[PDB]
Image 1 (cartoon, rainbow over the protein chains, first blue to last red):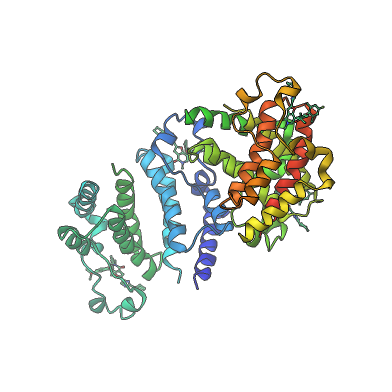
Image 2 (image 1 turned 45 degrees about the vertical axis):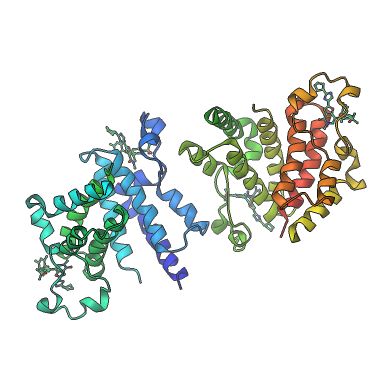
Length: 110
Length: 108
Length: 110
Length: 108
Ligand SMILES: Cc1cc(F)cc(C)c1Oc1ccc(C(C)(C)O)cc1-c1cn(C)c(=O)c2cc(-c3cnc(C4CCCC4)[nH]3)oc12
Ligand SMILES: Cc1cc(F)cc(C)c1Oc1ccc(C(C)(C)O)cc1-c1cn(C)c(=O)c2cc(-c3cnc(C4CCCC4)[nH]3)oc12
Ligand SMILES: Cc1cc(F)cc(C)c1Oc1ccc(C(C)(C)O)cc1-c1cn(C)c(=O)c2cc(-c3cnc(C4CCCC4)[nH]3)oc12
Ligand SMILES: Cc1cc(F)cc(C)c1Oc1ccc(C(C)(C)O)cc1-c1cn(C)c(=O)c2cc(-c3cnc(C4CCCC4)[nH]3)oc12
């Protein structure tokens, strides 16, 4: 019923992680390494971080009831990025490109 | 309505002359009959557009910013759902959504 | 201070991740890749998975409110190991050795 | 109550003759006076042992399995808190805790 939804959501997640979109997806593969980047205020501004490895773990853990919940985390990931950064920063451009793939594939599911 | 105040400012921003180049297909409902898109309402169960959002906003219908975001995203998802990716209107939806998602994510 | 006992919790996690314990801690660094190992029953038996990187990620994100919450997850990680496995499989021996490090350092906090 | 019955079986097992070689220091309270221990009650403010636990099981003072766990864990935790890591009692505590943690983990 909605296990078919989550099966399609799993397919989206594979696409998002795939090599073809890697030039814009790579900054969302792992949690932002605030420490390495020298960002003292990242966890002050982003209360609930999110990234695709996390989304994958929750997928495998069956933590998502339905596709809305999947989509809420994926959008959280992008919004965090837009929230933290100025609009001229390369990571924002990249988030936009990857959200295009996501919004498209998520619109086409049953 | 503190959080909704900024949502109303976003709406205003989406309707402004500056984004009209790519915002205009979303001002009114899609005229499916006029375009001869006979399958539009078969595929799109819940049509959405900026004037409908504005109508809702003017009437104090949004409870919180999450309801407002849901309708705006509904508008874009509808566009993406119905259309092939090569179509200009999808390129325009994406350009308008970038404006929306950015301004939404800076909500105080 | 809850942040002072969370600082200590952090110290413990650093201890758990250190090289002295790598011989036994390594099966707990990442989540158990059930899908990759062909453990079709794993997620049926284990409703809430845990591992050290998931703890680290929750620490970093300030998801833990006190030390008792930190400890609950670490014990969940080990319980899951004990629940899914027979008592003679090596991963059980390794879990015990790592739990023995954890419980001791947890006991020593103010 | 289905699970308190399974907990009682666990306590039964912790108290059985099998595990006596490492369980005996946990059968009754630490006799601090006898051992030569000025500071045991300063450092350990919530004493616990298997007999204590046994009474609370008989008196039906445990609401669920997790309250039962908490007490058994406390007993061990006390032993680890008070003692240096090389003490024979710590090694015995560990052997017994390995029995407890395993059977608790198999609770249906
Ligand atoms: C994509 C990209 C291009 C760059 F040129 C520089 C950075 C930092 C960059 O972002 C990242 C680079 C590396 C990493 C690692 C691998 C360490 O986790 C993460 C990012 C990154 C990912 N995401 C989702 C982000 O939102 C942000 C945000 C930032 C960031 C770095 N510096 C800022 C400052 C810049 C001045 C004002 C904000 N923001 O870096 C990332
Ligand atoms: C934006 C745009 C650019 C073009 F070059 C041509 C069209 C039709 C076009 O779209 C519209 C033009 C006018 C109007 C009016 C004013 C009548 O409401 C609506 C659209 C339009 C808006 N939105 C949101 C849409 O999703 C679609 C979709 C279409 C459309 C027309 N023909 C198609 C087919 C082509 C094969 C499969 C899709 N789609 O038209 C619109
Ligand atoms: C620790 C260990 C030693 C071995 F000699 C073989 C394996 C598979 C092994 O376990 C793992 C190996 C790799 C990984 C990766 C890195 C893929 O996440 C995980 C484990 C592993 C971690 N934890 C915490 C576990 O509880 C279990 C359990 C198992 C496991 C594999 N096959 C079984 C069945 C076989 C029949 C009875 C149990 N259990 O593998 C892991
Ligand atoms: C298990 C064991 C082996 C030994 F070789 C020596 C002791 C004291 C020992 O522990 C106990 C021996 C007897 C008893 C009696 C029967 C009197 O209640 C208790 C213990 C004992 C139980 N538990 C749970 C404990 O936590 C501790 C702790 C100690 C203890 C005594 N002296 C020390 C050292 C630690 C550094 C300061 C002196 N630790 O003894 C016990």
